[PDB]
Image (cartoon, rainbow over all chains, first blue to last red):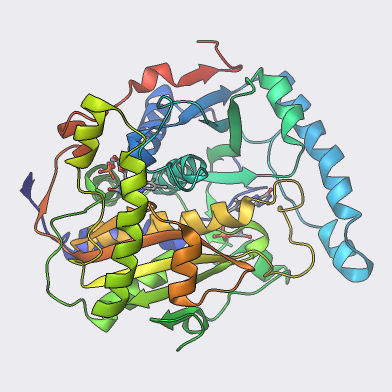
Length: 219
Length: 219
Ligand SMILES: Cc1cc2nc3c(=O)[nH]c(=O)nc-3n(C[C@H](O)[C@H](O)[C@H](O)COP(=O)(O)O)c2cc1C
Ligand SMILES: Cc1cc2nc3c(=O)[nH]c(=O)nc-3n(C[C@H](O)[C@H](O)[C@H](O)COP(=O)(O)O)c2cc1C
């Protein structure tokens, strides 16, 4: 190991700037393809996330064809109407007004998966909670989401669809599970607070109400 | 919604630095207490994470007492004994020589939970994959891991336990699930590559092997 400590004031500020201004983007994606170099940078950041037992359970399928985007978007529509019919009155009306994906518009999409069987028979750290491998994959997603913002690339996670329909589109095996579908593209503008808060779907919870001391429920 | 774009060369480098140099720390934690302000910043960061339907399913149980850390440590050991047992001969010995937690060393520990029933009867984006709320919570963890790195603070995830045991020690309800136990403390030395690689457990996988173009298995 080598010497380490806190970043400089400017370095820490750049770190919190990405964490604080990254948004989940749906409708602001610009049409320019992301350079090959920029993509390698984004995947690299993801590849450096931590992973249980250093399993590195992830795979990334790059999707850049209209044909594929169309099939995925339709799978979204089928699922989204279904989700829509799970609400009523004004909350349903409000649900149908939200943009929940940017699939056909984002010049790039990425389906991040988790190979449940990588790492051999037994994987360190996943001996007691088997979901840790999936969680590892999410860490890879956030690292990319954060790297993306710094590059001025908007990223949007889309989870509205029946998994099996997507695995069919991409040919993903049974031992591999989809963790996320991500829409990517440059942006020249972002919301300053979560879009769902601005559109009145749900507001930011008071952090002070979610922190306990020693025991659950104890402030 | 306002104008936005890529970070400056220096800001981008800072974000990538945290991403590339952060590690899972187990045995280098320092006894020095973290200030309440430093803890607010780390928690603030996590709370800036994305969350399905803006669910914000997380809660953070700060642990700072010797007695709690002792009970939690015993839990770890039992779990870890039965885990080591799952490896044979050569590998088992290697497993046993690894340090997989700094529960007793870390001056601060944080149990990050996910309330499966928050957000109402139905929660946006979580109508097809009921796991999206846990995934959201992992995003919170990764933001805290990254901010912590910039603060010169180390973070170590420990998942080798029998969850039911930890829930009982912290008095966590049935509708709430533990996503992660994070050990925290200042750190002045960090491995230059994942500790498990340096110790011969698993090497870094070749990213080129995990990226596909358009469909699974296609280069
Ligand atoms: C696991 C997960 C799944 C998500 N799925 C969707 C989705 O399907 N459609 C969508 O518009 N947003 C989706 N989101 C984004 C949240 O709605 C978003 O985090 C929040 O409303 C805005 O957060 P932000 O302003 O930090 O981006 C998802 C987020 C997470 C963490
Ligand atoms: C979901 C998850 C659970 C983990 N659980 C443990 C654990 O129980 N004990 C441990 O020593 N490390 C644990 N780790 C850390 C990994 O072993 C470590 O991230 C990897 O070997 C190299 O990580 P780094 O690049 O962060 O150093 C966990 C990581 C993840 C993502």
